[PDB]
Amino acid sequence: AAANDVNYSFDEAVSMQQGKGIVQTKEEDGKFVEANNNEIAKAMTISDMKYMDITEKVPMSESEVNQLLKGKGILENRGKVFLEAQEKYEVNVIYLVSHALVETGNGKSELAKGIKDGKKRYYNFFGIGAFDSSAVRSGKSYAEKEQWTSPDKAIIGGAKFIRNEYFENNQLNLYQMRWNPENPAQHQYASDIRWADKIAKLMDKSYKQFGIKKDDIRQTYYK
Ligand SMILES: CC(=O)N[C@@H]1[C@@H](O[C@H](C)C(=O)O)[C@H](O[C@@H]2O[C@H](CO)[C@@H](O)[C@H](O)[C@H]2NC(C)=O)[C@@H](CO)O[C@H]1O
Ligand SMILES: [Cl-]
Ligand SMILES: [Cl-]
Ligand SMILES: [Cl-]
Ligand SMILES: [Cl-]
Ligand SMILES: [Cl-]
Ligand SMILES: [Cl-]
Ligand SMILES: [Cl-]
Ligand SMILES: [Cl-]
Ligand SMILES: [Cl-]
Ligand SMILES: [Cl-]
Ligand SMILES: [Cl-]
């Protein structure tokens, strides 16, 4: 019956995002530092790729997706699998590619080449859970738990996670994934205050490259 997810005033949400121990980071002078309170408040202000529903699909062929992935390292020539993910889980493939490209350094980062454990290697292209050497051997790594033992398994698995844990939790766009205005400071995808902006920028370029129509835009989150 109750389908109202507007729960907090903006000032209430800001105070929550500024709460004790909550990690909020900003890229400065070549690396990540903790964001200050003013920066957090500014980052979460509403200004529109960041506000667009990414739980719908877009008309991109495997050829078009591989065009986007050309020259993208470990992600090059994996468009078939990104589209398997889109259709299986109803995840916007432009969003999915853009998120992967941000997180993996255009597919070229050292971490994108995975983490060794025994005879296997684990991959993670979406910043999901703990992903470093210690977590993998300790077994306390989501990528290991889900057995993302290849790049293709990491693409499909990443989409599954986003659908099941975010889209099914009513976090339908980048803003909601980052700032969870229905329940501020819980279940947020990333600590980088500009996480949504980085993904949205690549999304917008790809939308304009292929002439893709935008899905629903929502700008009301707060009382
Ligand atoms: C996708 C991912 O793993 N993101 C990290 C994020 O975890 C989210 C919430 C997730 O598992 O989907 C993580 O957020 C913290 O997660 C711990 C559980 O691991 C929670 O106890 C904290 O409440 C979370 N904080 C917030 C604000 O949601 C953050 C922590 O910086 O890192 C993300 O990369
Ligand atoms: Cl603190
Ligand atoms: Cl946190
Ligand atoms: Cl094609
Ligand atoms: Cl690197
Ligand atoms: Cl990420
Ligand atoms: Cl984990
Ligand atoms: Cl939540
Ligand atoms: Cl944002
Ligand atoms: Cl334009
Ligand atoms: Cl379209
Ligand atoms: Cl609002």
Image (cartoon, grey):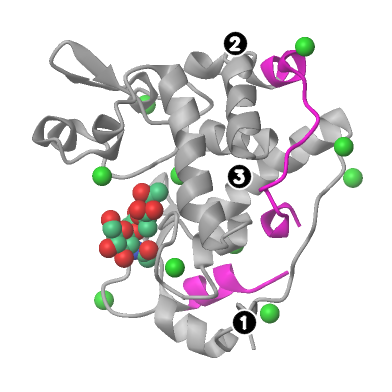
The percent coordinates of residue 58 (x first, y second) are 77, 35
Q: Which residue was labeled with disc 2?
A: 77
Q: Quadrant of ligand 10?
A: top right
**Local secondary structure at mark 1:** loop
Q: Confirm whether the magenta stretch covers residue 221.
A: no
Lower sequence index among marks 2 and 1: 1
Residue sitting nearer the eye, 145 or 96: 145
Residue 69 position (above or below residue 19): above
On the image, the x and y values in percent for residue 89 come to 58, 37
Q: Position of residue 136 (x, y in %)?
A: 18, 32
Given the image, on which type of amino acid does mark 3 rest? Ile
Type of the residue with mark 2 = Asn
- Would residue 189 be found to the left or right of residue 2 on screen? left
Q: How many marks?
A: 3
Q: Is residue 51 within the magenta segment? A: yes
Which numbered disc covers residue 199?
A: 3
Badge 3: few (under 14), some or many (20 or more) residues near its Cα, within 10 Å? Answer: many
Q: Earlier in the sequence, mark 3 or mark 1?
A: 1
**In the rendered image of this protein, does residue 23 appear above or below residue 202?**
below
Q: Which residue is mark 1?
A: 2
Q: What is the magenta range?
A: 38-67
Label drawn at residue 18: none
The N terminus appears in which quarter of the rendering?
A: bottom right
